[PDB]
Structure formats: C-alpha cells, structure tokens
Image 1 (cartoon, rainbow, N blue to C red):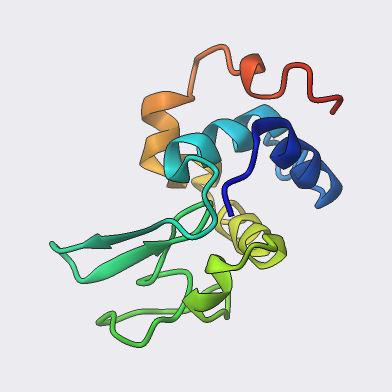
Image 2 (tube, rainbow, N blue to C red; image 1 turned 180 degrees about the vertical axis):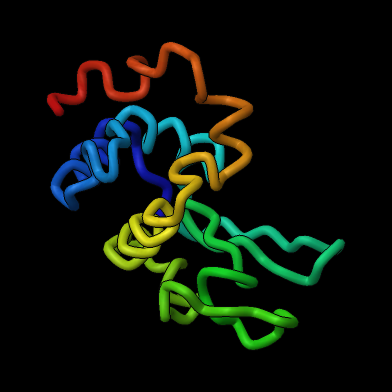
Length: 130
C-alpha cells in the first residue's frame, strides 16, 4: 500500500508514535518519506552484505526481522520480515519503536541524518490535523 501523507500521519499518531522516546511525529514522517516513500511493500537488497530492508521503515534483516537467508542475523523485533510488508503497519511500527529503544535512537537510520536532522520538518505533518 502507498500511503497518502496525512493518512499516514494520523495512522502513526493513533499508534502512539508522537513523542515516542523523544521523537516527534514530523520526524517519523520525514523518515518514512525518505526510507520508502510511504510504500509498505518497499524492499531493498544490499548486495554488499546479503541483507534486505523491508517495509515502510526499511527494517533490516540482519538485526531486526528474520528472512532466513541473511548470514549472522539476529531478529530483535522477533518478527518474520514478511510482517513488515503488510498493508497494516502495526507490526512495522512496533519494530520501529524497538529500533529507537537502542541508544542511537532515531539516528539508527542514516537517511534520517542526511535528510531530516537539523531541518524544518513541519511540512511533513502540516494540515493533517495531528
């Protein structure tokens, strides 16, 4: 499923993402935008290390979810990577909350540093009623 901006914003707020571990809703929106373009079936194979990124937040198979073909993989979210490909993003959101419980927080995603950090991110939630 490809979410429309405000639709996703309201969905994330209902799932308790606003302010989760100090992270504003606009930051979560900026992250999903650059990670998958708000596309729940987005997948990306990393030829260099044999891992694959899955879903709206691009959860990696080496650390976060299990796909069975990634060497030395841990499954910190205790989820099959298939779970991060559903139209219902409850599981993808639960795994993203898990990622930020680590010390790096939102910085765990390099894309956030490149495209969101120290910028005006209000635009991601403007007019959404959240």
